[PDB]
Image (tube, rainbow, N blue to C red; front, top):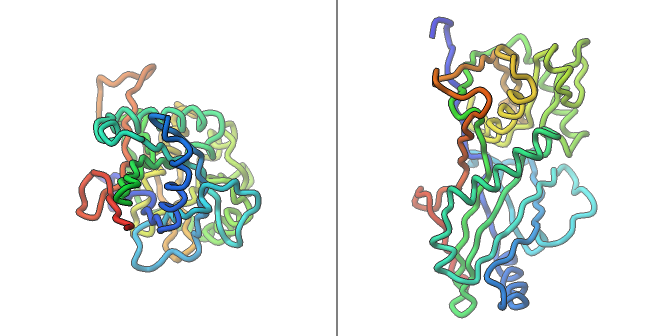
Length: 291
């Protein structure tokens, strides 16, 4: 807290769920075929439209419909595909008593394992559900596994406006490279795919951000920064670009720091979070009456 404008970076939830009636109708149809099972997990695909996020939003909407259950074969115009899954529980008591922290931690571990192989694959979402087919009442809860490893590492940042010139090229790069969440500068300031050997030298990382909150990036940022630390353990100071398709991109002069002296360097804890808040702002399932 000596440099002016130095702050610890804070975050916003990565997505907001919007499940339309066709999603619940399809969930219902499919559930009728698995009544003998205690639970099922089925892949989902959604299309993110980072160019047309409503002004009223705080983060990108995650639109679930009947089509989300379908195999996605081709990209929709101006939209980025995101894979997730739905875990449907046929016993309401199990839906309720499932330890949600453990469950999301398990999801996060898979994102982590994917991410340390390819940083662009550490993003996902999960829906847990119970569907009362008699009442046509549906309980659901969106989780977006966000992991901070080490749990005790924070990111100190201040604005780096001298980098603002890069925003346009980053927007265009993310448009073209629709399967990627991050890009970096190479040693000649060309925008390229993340490469752990290049970034260790060039130290400039840009992220496709899902938040629209001013100066506050998506919590998904935590995932990317955890992978970065694993990839480049000696990296302390670097430049971080938070890229949005609106006018809200921002660049940061960033510094990793630990708030725990007795923290394990060989076996750091991973903090996991990302359950969506419900209509009342509580960390609990949402309930929809479709009858």
